[PDB]
Image 1 (tube, rainbow, N blue to C red):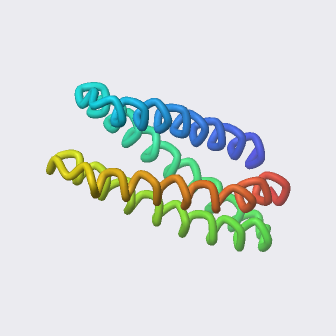
Image 2 (image 1 turned 30 degrees about the vertical axis):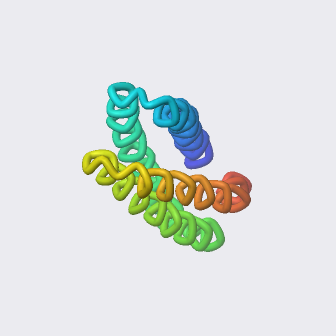
Length: 126
């Protein structure tokens, strides 16, 4: 069902949270080799999550589930804010700009935390 597809998507999102937190520790510790690997892992996780969310939104549209569509349109817009910040963080790591990396890291945390009430709303709406 679309609901079980959302739970699978939510698990992928939680995997990115876990990897993000271990990447933040590695960055603090200056373990740049680890950070590089975690950033590649996160890019793959965010790509997969984005694809699953788009399939969920498309399915809700085909089902005529107007409320789920509204919430998913809002949530996917917020996902793209997070993705833009993530990509900037990756660039800051490539460039050696730790000040920017820290800034983007905290912003990705706040964007993600803000977006969680809506994430739970979507589960109930599908």
